[PDB]
Length: 182
Image (cartoon, rainbow, N blue to C red; front, side):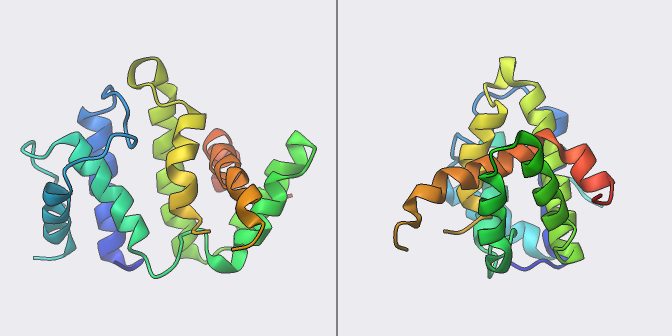
């Protein structure tokens, strides 16, 4: 879809359902649902407050969220900033990495930053319940790295860092999204 009020609506409805009734489900966002049911939920989420019905499986609701993200004209992190995000995740200093990424996040247009904020806040909660759902920060990075940054030469060796970027955003979401860079 697009980054319009419908998009934020879809994300919020999906985040809410996963948190209020699927936080303990194993393999959240790793386990794929039945494409048939996914597309059907999506079509209902596009247009005629409310909340997803219990009739919908969690695997279906998390898959809806991921496919919606892959349907955006461009990656949420933006083609225009991708290279910068990868370069920052490479810094040898564990702290220089957060600073650069922090600054890069605040340069994104409001809408990308906002959706990215809702997503990372939510994933941090998912990850904190890893003993039960098995989804650690690293495991979430693998699922969302290629979904938020759409990757052709020798750049194949930087794919791994796309995942590190998501990890950094999950682990430092409070600082990165709730404060302005130094």
